[PDB]
Structures are given as C-alpha cells and as structure tokens.
Amino acid sequence: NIITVTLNMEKYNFLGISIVGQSDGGIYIGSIMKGGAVAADGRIEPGDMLLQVNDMNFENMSNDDAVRVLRDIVHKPGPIVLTVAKSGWKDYGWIDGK
Amino acid sequence: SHMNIITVTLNMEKYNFLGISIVGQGGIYIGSIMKGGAVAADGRIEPGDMLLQVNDMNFENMSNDDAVRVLRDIVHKPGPIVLTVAKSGGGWKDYGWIDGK
Image 1 (cartoon, chains in turn purple, green):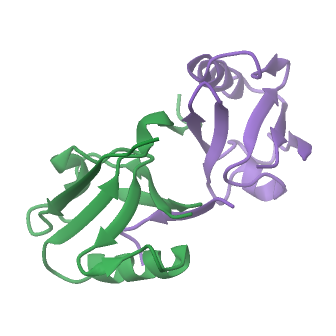
Image 2 (image 1 turned 180 degrees about the vertical axis):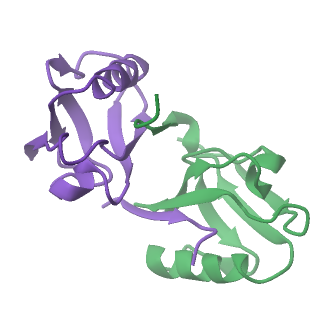
Image 3 (image 1 turned 90 degrees about the horizontal axis):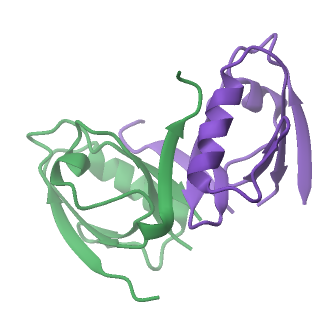
C-alpha cells in the first residue's frame, strides 16, 4: 500500500520524474526518466501518489503548493526520502517515437 | 459526469509531429502536450482527455496496447490525422518534469 524510498542522490544527480495533479485529490508520478534516481531504485511507478518528501507531507496541501515545495526541496543538494501510496497506469511516452 | 466530445483534424503536413504523450489506465489518455506540434497548434485537446478514435480505428473494443500501436503506425505514415477525444481532462494537470530549475 505505502512505500518509502531513500534515493541515492550522490550517485544519481536527479530524480527523473514528472508530476500530474488530479482534482484537489493529490499529486502523482506521471513519467519516470531512465537514468534518474527514481528509475534506479525501481520501487516507484507511474500513477503512484506522492505523500511526503523529506519533512514535507503533502496530504493537507493543495496540488500547486505540493509541487512548489517539491521543486524547492529537490533543488537543494542533499538526501531525498519519498513516500508514496502504491496506486493500472502505463506511460507509453511520446507518440512520435518508434 | 457528462463529457463533451470533439473531433479535430491534425495538419501533419504543416507540423511534423503530433506532440502528445499517451498514458493508459479504461482507455488511453493524453499525458502531456508539446507546443510546436500539431495537437498544440489546434489547441483544443488537453492533458487528461481520453482518445476515442483515430481515423477509422475506434478504441472502445481495443486494448490500450493495441490502441497505441495502431495510433503510432498512423502517425508514422503521411496524411492528416482525424482524432476524436472525450473532454475528460478537466481534473488533470501536467506539472512537467520536476528536475529543471
């Protein structure tokens, strides 16, 4: 149901995730970039709902506030701990690809 | 609960790409739209809208994988592309990649 992941932000230098807001319902992992810390770890998937990053818990903030705070946190060097709710969502990428 | 539906014809000769990503859930949906492409140029389709039909291929009785494969095939052949979408995206906001400053 819930998974917490501590990301290797020394080896990897970026999370490599997009965010989708649903409404406010919450913010969700949209796409994952191969080569980033989240892809490396492997436990988080597209459609998972983001609950907390570091000391910032998103459950009682607006989607826009959540993404604002998330951006600020991920652009400070240092450790990143993400907690998600494991929520049938497949990313096919750009249709203009082979 | 009601959704509007729209049909749009994409001018692929003028634009060289559609500029949409697709996510499957139920159905296939627009994930993101890249400005510069044919879909953004038309302007009516938004992230979270559901694709119903491309040209003569209706997706109601197709798996998401088969829908995307058929769409991708069409995109890689010349000609205009006629897309019908359900306006289901009202509650879906694409914030983009978190990684850039």
